[PDB]
Image (cartoon, rainbow, N blue to C red):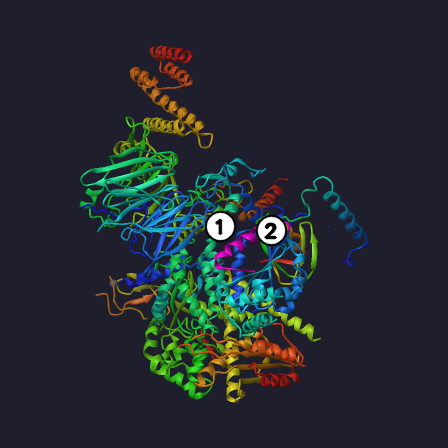
Amino acid sequence: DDDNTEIIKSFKNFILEFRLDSQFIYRDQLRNNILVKNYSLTVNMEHLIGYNEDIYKKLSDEPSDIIPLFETAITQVAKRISILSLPTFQLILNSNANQIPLRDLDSEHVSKIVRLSGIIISTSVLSSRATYLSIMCRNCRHTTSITINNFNVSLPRSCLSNCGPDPYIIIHESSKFIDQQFLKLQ
Amino acid sequence: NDTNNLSHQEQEYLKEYCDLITDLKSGDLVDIDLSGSLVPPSDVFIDVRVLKDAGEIQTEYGVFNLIKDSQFFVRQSDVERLIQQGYLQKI
Amino acid sequence: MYYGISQFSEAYNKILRNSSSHSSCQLVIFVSCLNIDALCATKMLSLLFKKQLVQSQIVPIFGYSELRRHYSQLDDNINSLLLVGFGGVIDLEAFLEIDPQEYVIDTDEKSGEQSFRRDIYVLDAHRPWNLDNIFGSQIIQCFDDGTVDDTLGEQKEAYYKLLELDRKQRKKQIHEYEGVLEEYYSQGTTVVNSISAQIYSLLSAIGETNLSNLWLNILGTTSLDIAYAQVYNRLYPLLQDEVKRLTPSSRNSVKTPDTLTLNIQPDYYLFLLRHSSLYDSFYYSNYVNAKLSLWNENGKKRLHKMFARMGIPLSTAQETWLYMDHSIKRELGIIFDKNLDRYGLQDIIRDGFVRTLGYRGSISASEFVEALTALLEVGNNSAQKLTNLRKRWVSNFWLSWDALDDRKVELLNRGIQLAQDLQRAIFNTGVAILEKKLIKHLRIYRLCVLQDGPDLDLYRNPLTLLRLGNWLIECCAESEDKQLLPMVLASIDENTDTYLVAGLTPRYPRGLKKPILNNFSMAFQQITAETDAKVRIDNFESSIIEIRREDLSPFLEKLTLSGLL
Amino acid sequence: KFRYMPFSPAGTPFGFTDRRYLTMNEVGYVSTVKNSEQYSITVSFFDVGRFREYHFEDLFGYDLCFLNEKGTLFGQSKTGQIQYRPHDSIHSNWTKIIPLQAGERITSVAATPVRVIVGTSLGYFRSFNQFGVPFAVEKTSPIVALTAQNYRVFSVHYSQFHGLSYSLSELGTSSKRYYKRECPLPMSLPNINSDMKKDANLDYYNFNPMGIKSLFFSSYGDPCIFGSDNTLLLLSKWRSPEESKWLPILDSNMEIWKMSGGKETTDIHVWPLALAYDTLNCILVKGKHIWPEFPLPLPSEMEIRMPVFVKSKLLEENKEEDKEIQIPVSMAAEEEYLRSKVLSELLTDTLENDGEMYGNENEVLAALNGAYDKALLRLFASACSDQNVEKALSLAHELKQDRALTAAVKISERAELPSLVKKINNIREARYEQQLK
Amino acid sequence: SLPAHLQQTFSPEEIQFIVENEPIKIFPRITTRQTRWQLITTDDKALNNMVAMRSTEVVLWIALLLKQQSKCSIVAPQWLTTKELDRKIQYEKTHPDRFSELPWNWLVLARILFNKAKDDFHDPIHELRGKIQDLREIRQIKVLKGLKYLNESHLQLDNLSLLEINELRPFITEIMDKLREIHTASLT
Ligand SMILES: [Zn+2]
C-alpha cells in the first residue's frame, strides 16, 4: 500500500527540482504547455537516469505498472503551478537506447520498453475509449463510478446497497472518453 | 556618418542630413559621442577574437595588429568601434 | 639566462613591473598549436593575468617558419614575450638576428645586469638545451627543473673555458672542451617534464590554487601517459595529494544541481569506456589489440570467449554504457578480478581521476584528453595550398580552447563523437597494413610506406599520423620478444607529390631502467645538410620531415647507409 | 576528573574527519590535513593585500600553534619540538627541541616581536629571544592559556592546590613589568554540566577540559575572555590595582533568546573571533557540532549590551510567530545609560594613558556623553511623570550639560513640579558657580 | 534616430543599469584609511575611509567591481533568506488578491547576486533558487487573473516589481488605449 505513495512522491520531487544550469526545464515546460491547452509532458530518459538511477530501474523493470503512477504525479504538480478542472496528463518519452531490428523481436522482450523503426503502411480511423465512467445498479437503483486507465478490466460483480448477481449498467449521459488509433509498421 | 536605388533628390537629401549630423557632433556637446553605442556599459575589460585580416591599424587609444584568429584581452571602450565595423567578436 | 624553482616568483614580479602600462599591449604570448600541454599551460596563465588586469595578446603558432614571421613584425613597446612549448634546443640569438646592443636600455653598474627593452621567456621540457640559451644569452630567460645545475658542471665548465680560451697546453685544452661539448651535443632527444606542472608550482607559490587550476594541471599531465609513461609515473603521486587536499569536508553528501566533485577511483586503459559500449571499449583499446591480436578472427573469437566466461550476455555488452543494466555496472569491478588473469590481461586495472558536475554525469581525465585531441585533428601553387592547410589547423586551436569551459559542454560532446570515428578509421588501416604484410624488415630499423588507402588524407595531419604510429608500435612491441627497433612511417600526398615522414622509437611494455632517446633528429639533420633532395624541416618536433616523391628512395638510401641510426 | 591538555586560541577537534582548524584570530587562521603518516598545513589571512596565503608539509605532527602579523609559531607537546616562521622570507625559519621530564608536556606557547615563551603541565616556564637565545626559566602554577598584543601579555594558570588564577605583564624593551601575578580568576567552570548532563559533546570537553572557549586582547589592548557559560568578560581598571575589576559585558544566550522570539533554539551556537571596539566578530554555527568547518563560513558582527533583562517580565510585557520580543523603554534607557557610562570610562582610560591612534576618538567620546545624558533625561522624565521628586532630583545630579538641565527644567514644568524646577535651578546655579570658579 | 524597440519602453539592460545605482553593504579586506577615488556621481568619503573587516555601504556597481577581485565581500540583504521567503510565500497563499510586499528590485538583485556572489551566502543556494521560483509562479497566477479588468478608465497595482511591470507594459497599455478609443468615439 505505501509503495504506491513513495513512488508518486519520488516522481513529483523529480519534476519540481531538475535544474541543468539555471532553468527548471520541466517546471517551465509543464507551465508553457497548459497555456496552449496541451495536457502532456515530454520527459527524456537521460535526465531521469542522471537524477536518480533507482527510479529508472523501477521504470525499466515494470513499465505497465509504473507509467500510470508517473502520470498522476504530473497532474499533482500541474495544479500547484496554475491554481490558487484538469484531465489526467499524458507522459511522453525520448530515448537513445540501441534500436532493435523489427525482425529480431521475440519472447524475450514481452512487457519491456523497446525502441525500433520502420515505415508506416496503414492508419485506422479514430475510436473512443473510456477513462471516467459512471454506473447504475439495476435492482436498488444505487449509483457509483469507476476510473479506467489504458495499460495491460471488465465490469464488476460486487453488487452494492440481495442486490443481485450482475446488476450494473453504464450511464453514458455522465461519463468521459478519449481518442484511440491503430497503425501498422513495416 | 550603393547609391543607385535612391532618386537624385534623395541622393542630395542624404548628404545634407550627414552635414547636419556632423555639425551637431562638433562644437559644444562634443565630449559625448552622439553616434556611439546606446547599450549601457556592462564591463570595462573583455576578451575579443580577431575575425578579419585588416593588418595593422591606428586608433585613438593606440595601434593594433589584427593577426587572423589571435585573441586580445582589452578594454571595451577602445574596441567598440572595431566591433561595430566587424573586425572583432566578443568571446 | 635560466632560473630555478626557488626563483620563479621573481620573474613573475619582474613581468608585472615591466608590462605595467595601459596605453599599449605590453605583453604577448606565443603558443605552439598541436600540443595539449601547451594549450593547458596557456589557459592557466591567461586566467592568472586576467585576475591581474594585464592587457595582452595570444597568438597560436605552427612552426619555425611562422615563428620568424611573427617575431619580425613586433612593436618596440612590447616589453615582454612568452614562448610556450618549443625552442629550448636551438640558439635563439642565432635563430633571430639578435644584436643585444639594439635592446639594452640600462646596465646596472653594480651587478652588471643589462636591462633589456624586450624580454623573452621560454617554457619547454625538451632536452638537452642549447647551452647558449642557458649561459650566454642574456635576453633569453628559461625555466629549468634544476636539471641544468644538477648535471651540467663539466659542460658549464667546458663552455666557459672554451669561450675564455679565445702550444701543447692550448691544444690539449681546446681538444678537451671540444670533446666535452661534442659529447653533450648530438645525443638522442628526450622530454623530461610537464609544462602545466611547473606553472602549478608557481601558482602554489603565489597562492592561487583552486579546483579549476588543479583540473587543468591533471589534464596537462594526463596527455603524457601514452608516450612517456615514465614521466607520468614520476608525477602522479603529487596529484593524489592535491586532490585529497582540496576536496571539501562532509564528503559523500547528497547531490544537488550545483554540486561539483573531483575524486580518485578506478580507470582502465579502455578506449572511452563511459561512452559507446563495453564491447567497443575492449574492441578498440590500443592495448587489447596487442594482447589478443584483434586484426584477425583467431583474435576476435578470444574476445567473444572472454565475455561468455565472464557471464555477461554478449547482446548486453554491446548496449550503450549509460543504458546498460545497473547490476552489471556495479558488479563489473569484481568480475574483472576473476577473469583477466586467464587472458594475460591484468594490466587493464589501475586508478585515475574522475569529475562530475551536478546531474549531467561523470567523465575521467583519460576520456577528456581524447576529446580534445580529436577536436584538434578534425575541427572545421603549392605554397598557397600549404598556407591554407596550416591556417585551417590553427582554427582548431580555438575550437579546442572554447571546450575547456563548463558552460560549453555541447562542444565537448561533438569532440567525443569525432574521437570515435578517428579511432575507427585508424583501426581499419592498421589491419590492412598487417594482413598485406607491408612492414619491410630491414636489418637496422623497420620501414613502412602507405602508397594508397581508403582515404589517405587523414594522415596529412601530424597528430593523426602519430596515432597510427602508436597503434603499430604496440603491435610490434608485443608480437615478438626480440628486436626492439626504430621505425619509420610515411604517407604520400597526391596534391604536393610529397611524402610526410615520421621517425618513431620503440618502448618497453606497460607492466615492467633509464629512458631511451629518439635519435632520428640528428640523422635527418645530417642527411638534410648533405642531400641533393628537395626537403622541408620546419616543425617543432624535428622527428617529422617532408620530401618529394622521386627523392624518397635516395634519401632513405643515404639514411640507411649512414651510421647515425 | 580534571587532566592537563594542550590548547591554542579557537581551534577545533578533528571530529570524524582528517582535518581541523588549529587557531583563529582577527588577522587570520590556520588549518591542517592528515595524509597517511604526514600532515599538510595551510595559513590564511583576512588582509589579502598585506600578506600571502601559503602552505607546507609537517612530518612531526604539531599540535600547538600561535599567530601574529610578524610570523607563526608551531609546537609539538609530547616531543618538545618547536618551529618559528616569519612572514617574510628574509629571516629564515628556525627550530629547536626543548627538554621535558617524564610525562611532561607543553600546554601553550606565545610570542611578542622579540620574545618567545613556552609553558608545561609541570608548571615550568621557559623564554627565548626571536633567535632562540635562552633568557630565563621560572617555576609557577601550571599554565593553561597565553595571549599577546605587541609588548602586552596575558596569562592564565590553574592548579588543584592553588585554584584558578591569571597574570598580566608588559615585556617592555626598556624594562619588563608585572601588573598582576597569579591573582584569583572569577570565571564560570563547566565541570558540573560535563559530569551530569552526558550530552555527547564530551569530545569538546576532552579537546578543551578547561572549557575556556577563547581569549584575546581588545582592539585597544584590554584583556578579554569568553566563558563556558557563553558570556564575554573584560577586565577594567587594570592600571590601578585597588580599582581593577571584572565586568560582564555580553551574554550570547540572551541575544539568541530574543532573536528567536523568546525561544530555545539550542541548535544555534556562537563562535567568537575578536573584539572590535563595541562589536563582537563571530561565526553563527548550526547543527550537531558547536564549532565551524571548511570551507570557512562568512563572519558576523554583534554589539555588546549590559545584562539587565528578565525573560518572564519581557514575556509579560510582550503579551510573525518568531518576532523578537518588545522591551520596556525604561529597560532600554537604563541599559543605554549603563553601556554609555562603561564605554566612555574605558575609552577615557585608553586616551588618558595611550592617547589617540587615529585622531577622532574624542568625537566618539563626546557622542557617548550625549547619549548618556539623553538616556538619563528619559529616565528622569519617567520619575517626574510618576511625581517621585526625590528620585527625579537624585537622577538630576547625574546629568552633565546645562542644555540637559534646561531640558529637565522644561520637563519639570510639564510635570507641574515647581519645587523640582526650583531645586534644579538651585543645582544649575550651584553648577554654574562651580563652572565660574 | 532612436531604435524602434526603444520608442516606448526600457530594455532589460537599462533595468539592470537602473538597479545598479542602489547602495549595498560590504566587508572590505583592505584598509584605505590613512591617492583617493574622487568620484563625481556618488559619495567619495566611504571608499577613501575603508578599514579591513569594518562594515560599510557603497553603490552596487562598485561593490561588484571590487568583488571581481579578492578585495571585497558582499553581505546579502536580509529579505534574501529562507525564513523571510517562507513567510512571503505564506502571505501570497493567504491573501488570494493582494501582492506581497517584496522590494521593487527583487528579481534583478537575486539574479545578479547568485551569479557574482554565490560564495557569500549563509543559506544553501540550492534552496533559495527554489523559493524564488515559487514566488514568481504564484505572482504569475495572480497577474493572469488581473488581465480580465482592462477598462476605459484606470487600474490600481501594488507591490508589483519593476521587471514584472516592464514585462507586461506594451500589452496593458495597448489594449487599454484601444478600449478608450472605442468608448470616446461614441460620445463625440
Ligand atoms: Zn444495491
Q: Are marks 1 and 2 on the same chain?
A: no
In the rendered image, the residue lying farthest to the right is B8
Q: For residue C108, which numbered disc appears in the image?
A: 2
- Magenta stretch, main secondary structure, is helix
Mark 1 is surrounded, within 10 Å at the Cα level, by few (under 14), some (14 to 19) or many (20 or more) other residues, namely: some
Which tag is nearer the camera, tag 1 or tag 2? 2
The answer to whether residue E141 is left or right of residue C532 is left
For the residues labelled 1 and 2, say whether their Cβ atoms are less than 8 Å apart: no
Question: For disc 1, does the CB lie below 8 Å from ligand 1?
Answer: no
Q: Percent from the top left, x then y, of residue D303?
A: 37, 35
The answer to whether residue E55 is left or right of residue C73 is left
The answer to whether residue C54 is left or right of residue A28 is right
Could you tell me which secondary element the residue under label 2 belongs to?
loop
Q: Percent from the top left, x then y, of residue C496?
A: 66, 79
| Magenta part of the chain | C1-23
Chain on which label 2 sits: C
Q: In the depicted view, which residue is nearer to us: B38 or B84?
A: B84
In the rendered image, the residue lying farthest to the front is C167
Task: Please determine whether, in this image, residue C82 is positioned above or below residue D412.
Answer: below
The answer to whether residue D144 is left or right of residue A127 is left
Q: Amino acid at mark 1?
A: Lys
Picture quadrant where residue D113 is located: top left
Q: Percent from the top left, x then y, of residue B54?
A: 69, 60
Could you tell me which secondary element the residue under label 1 belongs to?
helix
